[PDB]
Length: 203
Image 1 (cartoon, rainbow, N blue to C red):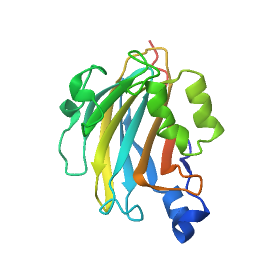
Image 2 (image 1 turned 90 degrees about the horizontal axis):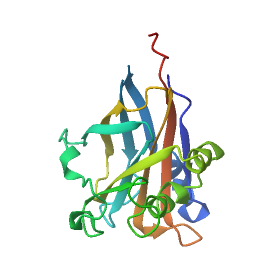
Image 3 (image 1 turned 90 degrees about the vertical axis):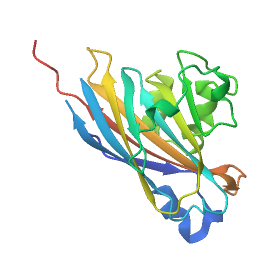
Image 4 (image 1 turned 45 degrees about the vertical axis):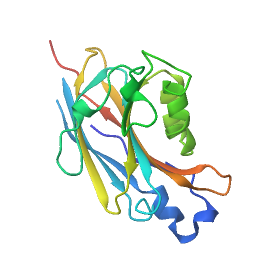
């Protein structure tokens, strides 16, 4: 029910012998997929120095799934921390928890394409991830700023299937530094992605 894990990053020779570690820092693992899908996202923050200069993480959901619950690495249900209206003042850039939606806004600072470009679009995404974006398969981004941990962080996400004629569901997650950059002066950014397949329900 899950395709092979995709990991990409814009880390390059400037990161030296951490390049490969930075590239393979994000993982996604299906827990259960049976009108609901539940998955875990793991960010290995060990080589990122977020306790010196903070980073951020992003969870990207496809059209056809609506997030119902997200639990952080402290087992705290943070679902209600995210705005639901992209233009809410509590969704501005000073805020720790932010939400972006292709149904609400595309370009501008709180647009889904801008925030893609600042996250997965920066992480040298592969053709599979780029085809999800160009085919308008992806729609929501949940973002957490002020990540300062140095361990592996696991988030557990649950979503409801909203499209009854859909079997394939791309899931993605991204982490970056907001200070350290690659040789091209772009924030070091890494991604993890897998596609989930649901069995067709007989009716």
